Image (cartoon, coloured by chain):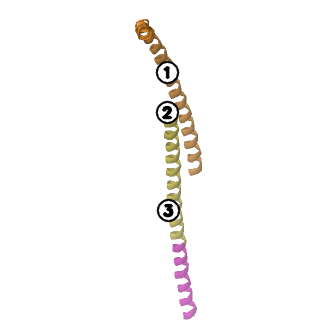
């Protein structure tokens, strides 16, 4: 009975670890893609202004 | 006859002592087996939970 309970607990723990790792990797990849697209959109929104500032710092 | 009867009474007392010793040995053996199985199951479940926690930590870091 102890060996059967140990085998069942190990299999259930491995299954729960695999499912939780899949869910956490999916949530991390979703947040990564969302934050990357949002940062690209925000940088494009803040763009075209300081380029002339860096050019005036560059041009004499 | 009286000495054989006294030796038979002592043999019955020894048989009762042997049955009591066998019962006490079986009880102590069952107690030790239950304690060993409880400690082993607790160690295995705690090891599975700790491995799951460490793997979840490394996966969240990744």
- Looking at the rendered image, the quarter that the C terminus of chain A falls into is top left
Residue B8 is inside the magenta segment: yes
Residue B21 pos. (x, y %): 52, 74
Viewer-proximal residue among A12 and B33: A12
Circle 2 is placed at which residue position?
B61
Circle 3 is placed at which residue position?
B31
The span picked out in magenta is: B2-21
Residue A54: which quarter of the image? top left
Under circle 3, the secondary element is helix
Chain under disc 2: B
- Residue extending furthest front? A60
Residue A5 is inside the magenta segment: no
Q: Do the residues bearing badges 2 and 3 touch, measured as CB atoms within 8 Å? A: no
Q: Which of marks 2 and 3 is nearer the N terminus?
A: 3
Q: Which of marks 2 and 3 is in front?
A: 2
Q: Calculate the distance from the C-alpha at mark 2 to the C-alpha at mark 1.
A: 13 Å
Circle 1 is placed at which residue position?
A32
Give above or below for A27 relative to A11: above
Res A35 visible: yes
């Amino acid at each position: 009975e102890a060996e059967a309970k140990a085998k069942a607990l190990e299999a259930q723990y491995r299954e729960r670890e695999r499912a939780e790792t899949e869910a956490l990797l999916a949530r991390y990849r979703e947040r990564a893609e969302a934050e990357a697209k949002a940062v690209r959109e925000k940088a494009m929104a803040r763009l075209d202004e300081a380029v002339a500032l860096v050019l005036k710092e560059v041009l004499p | 006859s009286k000495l054989e009867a006294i030796l038979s009474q002592e043999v019955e007392a020894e048989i009762q002592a042997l049955l009591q010793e066998a019962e006490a040995k079986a009880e102590a053996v069952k107690r030790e087996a239950e304690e060993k199985a409880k400690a082993l199951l607790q160690a295995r479940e705690r090891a599975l939970e700790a491995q799951y926690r460490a793997a979840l930590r490394r996966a969240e870091s990744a």
